[PDB]
Length: 324
Ligand SMILES: CCCCC(=O)N(Cc1ccc(-c2ccccc2-c2nn[nH]n2)cc1)[C@H](C(=O)O)C(C)C
Ligand SMILES: CCCCC(=O)N(Cc1ccc(-c2ccccc2-c2nn[nH]n2)cc1)[C@H](C(=O)O)C(C)C
Ligand SMILES: Nc1ncnc2c1ncn2[C@@H]1O[C@H](COP(=O)(O)OP(=O)(O)O)[C@@H](O)[C@H]1O
Image (cartoon, rainbow, N blue to C red; front, side, top):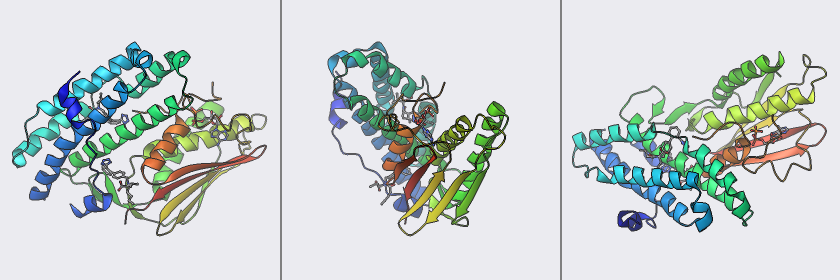
């Protein structure tokens, strides 16, 4: 029961708008944002410690959940022991602590879901697991974006202001993951569906690619796997996966349409649950794909919607909010 955690457990988070972040693209500005990072990170960690303290006693007593709760406390202690930033030199000392804590250990997400699974006999709230894991995933993504962005503001990459790409092409980032997915699918079945990309193929806009690097390969794997399992009798003649890009002033829509047989009526109300799967930080398998991708899409101001045509295929709509 530590009092420093209690002091910031209810303190509202301060999130800089990506628009404001793009404007800071800078010695006097890096000092101001570095001071902000130092003071924000313990508040984000204390919110998650408060989450562990609020679990029902029997669940919070799981040795895996308890071990993860201790990891959060130890991280809070390391981030608060560091003295307040006064100059550019103090700002640069804090970046190095941030890097060592970001690349730290365990694979917390994996341990948490394991602990929650071991405690399922004591879980009465049908939504407790889904809510705890959504909050854990979006909070850790928020922490990652906060820390990785500030570190990247010191480095100079073309077309980037920190982790924000100023000229992101959805077609290029989709193509990058299509090639990765097709190689894995080809190795497994001896073939892979071809992926066509249509719509606003020349669209380019400011966006943060990091969450797409989890979402796109997962959805592509889902569509390609469903197509192959659906056409096992003709494995060398399978229908294409068709991706459409729609770009407007409000959002970017990526529709991924397959002919993989659809998501059955009996599984539809389970596909968005953690651990639900029909296959034989956040993980890519074990039923994490869809709930993680949806939590990420909604955290970023968009959504992940599914339309199942049982017997034919599925259309998956990823919508993401524009920055300006
Ligand atoms: C209409 C504005 C849409 C902007 C948006 O996507 N929003 C969430 C968000 C904000 C900030 C980040 C972020 C980006 C880079 C580096 C760190 C952070 C961050 N994340 N957590 N702390 N810092 C990510 C998502 C909204 C907001 O909050 O402005 C909400 C209202 C939908
Ligand atoms: C300055 C870091 C403060 C936060 C911190 O120290 N930690 C959370 C954390 C760590 C790593 C990531 C991360 C980094 C790279 C790639 C993926 C992820 C990730 N991981 N999950 N989603 N994204 C995010 C958050 C602890 C830990 O987890 O080590 C805990 C014990 C407080
Ligand atoms: N495009 C799709 N077509 C058919 N079934 C799908 C599709 N996308 C997802 N599914 C179903 O939803 C389940 C859960 O998906 P997901 O959360 O990504 O986990 P995983 O990929 O680890 O199985 C899949 O195992 C599969 O049964």
